[PDB]
Each structure stands twice: as structure tokens, then as C-alpha cells.
Amino acid sequence: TGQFTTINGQVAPVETGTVDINGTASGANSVLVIFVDERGNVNYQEVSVDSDGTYDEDDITVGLTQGRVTAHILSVGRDSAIGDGSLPSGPSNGATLNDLTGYLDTLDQNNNNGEQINELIASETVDETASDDLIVTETFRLAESSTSIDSIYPDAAEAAGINPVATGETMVIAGSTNLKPDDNTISIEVTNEDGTSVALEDTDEWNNDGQWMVEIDTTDFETGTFTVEADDGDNTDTVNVEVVSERED
Amino acid sequence: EVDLEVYDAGVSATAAVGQDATNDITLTIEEGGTTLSSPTGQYVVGSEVDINGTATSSDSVAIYVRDDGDWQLLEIGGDNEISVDSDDTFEEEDIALSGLSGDGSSILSLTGTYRIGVIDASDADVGGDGSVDDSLTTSEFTSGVSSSNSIRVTDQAL
Image 1 (cartoon, rainbow over the protein chains, first blue to last red):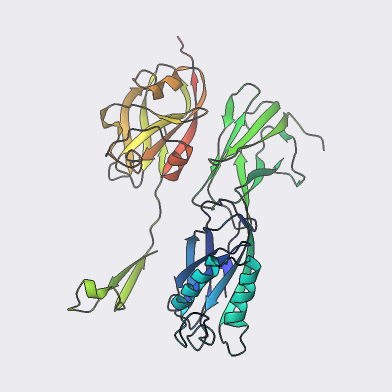
Image 2 (tube, rainbow over the protein chains, first blue to last red):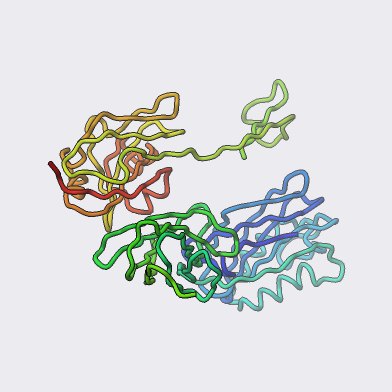
């Protein structure tokens, strides 16, 4: 069993990616994970599974190119050999996880399509009829970093995105992000018509759904137009909301 | 989660890298909290005020001021740090924020609404000599343990 944590199905920082892997691998001693892109570049890492077969490796960097990256998780089966041990360049019956890594180094060196690697990896290890090894498949689009504000509205029921907020009641703001839930944070700024900041809140926690909500009070706010600014050390999104004494209902 | 591994009697240090541990024990480690209390809400320009706050896991703390850019260091004076007692609390005498010399204080001189935050000694000149001498950016200030609160300066009175 395996899983991949994607903020929105994508990894934001292309230069320094990060994914979290966890699952159940009962009866195995080590688990190998491989990343391949559309060009054909390959990155691999072995994971030491604990005694009760519950492996959890966090903050795995991806050194591939921008585009679409498909991920596979390898696990030697009963034979404790990669499939049948019939590596194109490796020895017979000595095909371990480390041995298969040497075969991976030959894949990226040759000018092979990324789709060809998917056919080759499945055929040489799993598609063989005498193979006992198991894999799981997962894909994610490796894109650039993203941070945006989705919906701003008071404690009432609304999901359109924009809603005038009466002063004195707390209003919620919801946005999307691709950053790590804990290693990063989102700082907000609320400013009036002439650069007088009134509020400043930060959050450093959000589930793997990618949605984050920030609470700010409107006790001392004044009616008019207010600017909401959110930054995370990267591109900054700005949205404007109106403030009224009382709303229409 | 942090684990401790013991080994059988008579084993050497170099030869113990591969052999499995006879037993084990695990503990969890979390990050502490560093907040300010007194420099909050209002501040008369040119007035003096004490530095009040708490720091669970800290040895040296520094105070920074930010306004539409970098966190300029505030030169509090001696060693640019405050020690923490056993009660996880640190305090400083009455200090005039604008009165003290440094470019950090210059931001607070003009009337407006700003931000002030404290940070532990994890900076340590963002890598180098054991002294807090930098102007940490948003990423550097947020990366370490820290906390900031909104402050605005009000003109003088009589």
C-alpha cells in the first residue's frame, strides 16, 4: 500500500520539490520509489520499512524537469529478487533493489522517451509472467509554484468568492496553495484607502486538500474598500473587498 | 520522533553501525513559543517602554521591526540579546524604541502602523559569528521560531 501527498495534484517548486510517502509494506525489508518525467529522466530512492511494515518517508526531493511525472513504488516479492532476476545488464538471481538502480542509470543515459520507460519498467519487472513483485502507480503534474486567494465571505453561508462584510463580525478568507503545510506559512495584510494596515494574521497548517482559512476580526473596522494581501516569499496575490455597516438579507 | 539504540556489552563503536539494537526507546520533540506582550497596541513616539514576553526554548532573543520590506534589526544595546529565566520568561528594562541608535529605530520614528517581532538565537548571523547582526528577510525571519504582533505609533502628547 502506498500514497503520495499532492497539494493540488502538483508540486510547486520545480527547483526543489517535496513529496511525502507512506503506506503499509508487510513482509518487506526495503521499498524503492522511482520518478520519471515525459523526457525520460529518472530519480530513485530506497526507503527502510520498519518492523511492523509501516514505512513513512517525508520530504523527498524531486530533481526532474517541469511537466508530467509518474511515480512508482517498488517492492521485492517472495523471491526477494526483482521479478525473475532477468535484468538486461545485471546478473541472474542477484537482482535486488540496489541492483535495479544500476539498470536505471542506463535508462536515462540513452535517448529514451518517458513513455518508453513506463513500458520498459512494467515489462521487465512486473509484466513478466513469472514475476512476484508488486507496484502501485501514481501521477502528478510537476508545475511551477502557486498561491492564490479563492473565497472571502463572512461567517454566513456562501461559496461564490466575494461577499461584503459588516463590521463587528468575524469574516473567513479561503485560498489555495501548493507549499508544505508546516515548513512554510501564509501572511495576510489588510490595508485601508491610504496604506494604514489594520490586520495581520498568519497560518502554518492546512490539510492535504490545499485549502487554508484565515480568521480576522472586524470589530474596529470602518466601512469602505479594503485591500487583502497574501505573500509567502513568492508571487503575491491581492484582492479587494467592500465593508458596509449592515448587509442586505 | 527520536530514538535511542543500545548495543550488547563488549561491542566496539565502529562495529556497531550495522548490528541491530538490543532494545530501543523513542521520544518526541516539538518547537517552543516566543511571543512579546508589552510592545503591543499603541506606542507614543519617543516614549520608553519595557520588553515583556516569554520564550520556552531560547537563550538569546532579538527584536526586529518591519514595514513594507526587510526586518531591520533594532539595536537594543548590550549584546543585542535578552536571557531567559527558568520560568520561560524574559524581560528588559524601559527602553525608548525610537530614542536608541540604529536604522531599525528610524522606521518607528514616523507615525503609522507597523509590525514588531522577536526571534530566538537560531539566526546567529544567519550562519557565522555568534552575534545577531543582520536584517533578516521574511523567509529568514519566518523560518526560525518567532512571533510578530501589530503595532502603531501615535504622536506625542501633554
